[PDB]
Image (cartoon, helix red, strand yellow):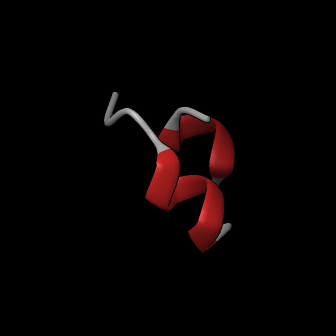
Amino acid sequence: VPCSTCEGNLACLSLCHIE
């Protein structure tokens, strides 16, 4: 889920925590 781990997948990045 976290935005540093989605890395350009806009679905993963939409669910995420911003860190």
Residue drawn 53% across the image and 32% down it? 2
| Vertical relation: 11 (above or below) 16 | below
> Residue 9: in sight, yes or no?
yes
Q: Whole-percent x and y of residue 13?
A: 52, 56
Where residue 18 sits: x, y (%)? 31, 36
Vertical arrangement, residue 1 with respect to residue 13, above or below: above
In the visual, does 14 lie left or right of 7? Answer: left
Left or right of 8? Residue 13 is: left
Q: Quadrant of the C terminus?
A: top left
Residue 6 position (above or below residue 17): below
Residue 12 is situated, as x and y percent measured from the top left of the image, at: 63, 55
> Is residue 8 visible in the rendered structure shown here?
no
Which image quarter holds the N terminus?
Answer: top right
Please identify the residue farthest to the front as the structure is shown: 15
Q: Residue at x 46, y 60 (%)?
A: 14
Q: Residue at x 62, y 66 (%)?
A: 11
Asked whether, in this view, residue 17 is left or right of residue 14, the answer is left
